[PDB]
Length: 245
Ligand SMILES: NCc1ccc(I)cc1
Image (tube, rainbow, N blue to C red; front, top):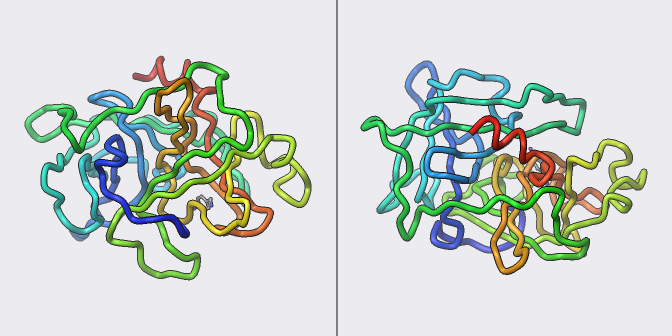
């Protein structure tokens, strides 16, 4: 997250931190995700497509720091890793950038809700907020495009939804942006998602309910004039989510 503010998992208790185990034992951060039910985390396919084996992954809930064991956290293996069969990528845009992880602890358990572990509601189909609505994004991704390191402490920021019509302008993204994607940005382009935020939640308030409106997917750079963050539009994937969970 470029700009914004530090936070803790209490302020986004559905946030899942996803890591990969390397061949020589090391463990590195991969991507964010969101707990949509006790056994299911939703994320982005592009996070996993290079290493698509479920046994490589570790998922944490209730975790506010990248490399420290937050009191109350839970650790899970990935029982199933479900990538979207119509995924594609070109130089910039990911299509159908959505993935499900069925989580299972070593004791064979799913998530147990606490002050630091809660689910996020899915949106109603084809029901998104209007352009200009402020939404929040959360993640452990880079604080500056040029950074080598990820922040140790979780971050969040606010971005505004951009109309498809605006996002499809040539000087924005043209036809790289589809109706299954949502664009969001800061009016001054000063805050955004960035590398390492992929898979994490774009959350908006619809009818007084926090709702998983988007999943962090792609962008040209980060916090860059005329280059919004692009998000998988969750409200256009409900049958896929329901059918795979
Ligand atoms: N600013 C949106 C964005 C940029 C790069 C990645 I990787 C993911 C999301």
